[PDB]
Amino acid sequence: QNFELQPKLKQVFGKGLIKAAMTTGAWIFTGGVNTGVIRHVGDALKDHASKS
Amino acid sequence: GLKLFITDDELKKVHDFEEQCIEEYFREKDDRFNSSNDERIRVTSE
Image (cartoon, rainbow over all chains, first blue to last red; front, side, top):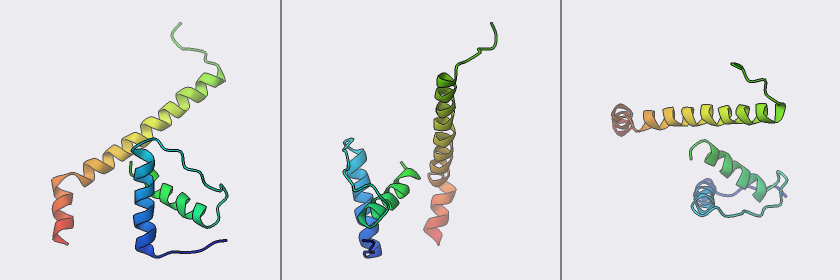
């Protein structure tokens, strides 16, 4: 289901997840569809794609 | 001889190469702006 976390928690978690993804070429395993934590990961990667 | 009549598969390849170039250019404009001295001083003032 869809949810929402703290804003600073979302920002810190998203920035750290995208850095952990790009420093090592990791594969991220999500559930695919745009709901919940996969939506948060997609917003984190949308923040990723504008910067690095 | 001059122009290359090109197949689609390679038209797609030159197209998304050019997409890579335009996106990388605008990111390079952005970090030239945000690493320029003027912008650093403006954010440090506010």
